[PDB]
Image (tube, rainbow, N blue to C red; front, side):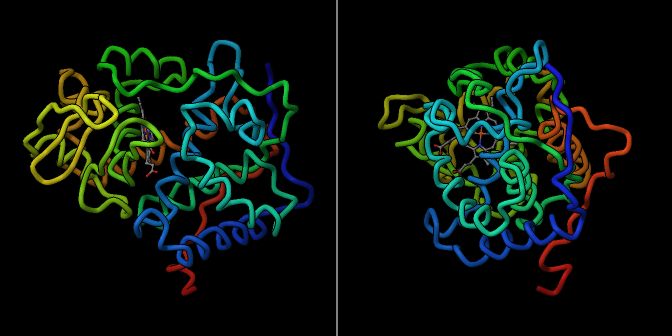
Length: 291
Ligand code: HEM
């Protein structure tokens, strides 16, 4: 399967910076969502789940085709709760009907991270919508109730290595688990709509307790009111993972730099970019624009 990036006709940096600003302006406006967390965390989760279907072996799945717009992927049990990120973006797609679905879902994730004061993420245009029959089947996204060997093995399919996996998981400092979506409940920290390295700090400094929640699932709970998933706590159980966790709890700039590279790579897996294709765009935030 080859998927070649095709820039939307005649579009350039300024067009996509207009779509960025539209998403970012609505993130500021619709602030009440999920008890004032706002839409940013569900939008970086949506960009991860449309990319996380990729399989390196046959180049199926991935962010290129925008296939989450089809019922099979929209109704995947693993995507429960992401309909709220879709409905947030649907106004903006009506306003810029020329951007492809893959591009709009991935730029929403980029915009949310930078607007929640994360690192800049280089983003590239050119994903092309593909037919309903290209939609990957349910079951390619990871279970939460498993251990470190499962996480390592699952992420080899998206060929991410240990460092990349640990840098990507730092995004679980954002938002929260919702019992009616996943059977898990609670936030992982106090700053859950500002991008920081707090996931790593909480993992190493809190007093975790294995408890059973109302959906009868086990999760790691702390006195402070935070929770960690079994696959999250996995990172301090494995010796290779645990020493990268310590590296990111001791250096927030290295965390930001490595997250930026692994999230771009995540979003680009499966796509062939021609050598005459434009460079990756670095978008300015509303704040850097005085907007
Ligand atoms: C083995 C890996 C992973 C598993 C099992 C997993 C699982 C989960 C689960 C069960 C939730 C709760 C969903 C809900 O109830 O609403 C969640 C939320 C979230 N995850 Fe993951 N995740 C994984 C990796 C990642 C990665 C790599 C990213 C992003 C780079 C990510 C970003 C998020 C975000 C931002 C949320 C919060 C959503 C919200 O607030 O609504 N996840 N994760």
